[PDB]
Image 1 (tube, rainbow, N blue to C red):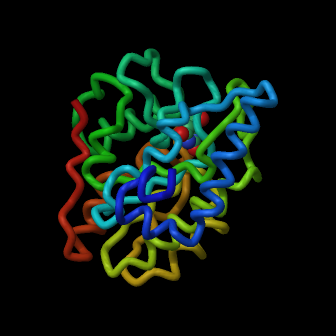
Image 2 (image 1 turned 90 degrees about the vertical axis):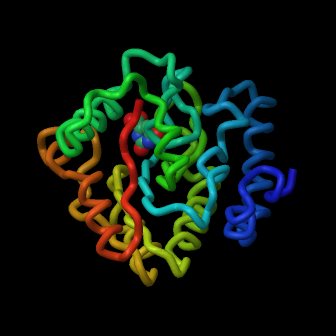
Image 3 (image 1 turned 120 degrees about the vertical axis):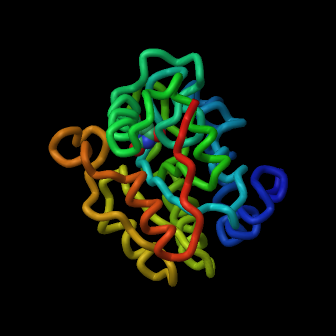
Length: 224
Ligand SMILES: O=C(O)c1cc(=O)[nH]c(=O)[nH]1
């Protein structure tokens, strides 16, 4: 399938510069199965963050690698399928900040699809992993794809708030700071930072203050 077939219209145009790289990663995953190795998430979920409208993205949440545990990774950073229990530690931590910052009760489950619908891009820098082998697909070719995605997002004549939850600020800030209406939430605690900087970081309320300050609508963060 060409990009226009795999991702939303705006994303297919945004990702044209890395269309050969996206083809190549498809070949890599087929070669992994031939090699007798597995990957997550499911092939159908790998580009899932790019199936929500490129023009409507208001917030970027950056992760590093998909969940390594079988049955966790669903192609949106930190999300899990609605029947997954208990939550992964990172997600439990995110939901504790969610209740504290926003005053909402604990979500009913770990499915962040509503954030994706509302223009929250849940982007991992690396979109696949070998099950039970954390960070096993680093350097396989995803970094160039997700860099093109972020630079394209930054280049829009449109507001963006970046939240960095994958700790690589010195690699990510240059891709973004080259934008016109991008605010980066600093500092950069990750959800596993927990009480050493993540809890009380107010990422959700701060993103809305920053969007309203750039003349955009806030995100409705409320999960079921
Ligand atoms: O393993 C994690 O907590 C994790 C999941 C995910 O999607 N992204 C990330 O950076 N970490």
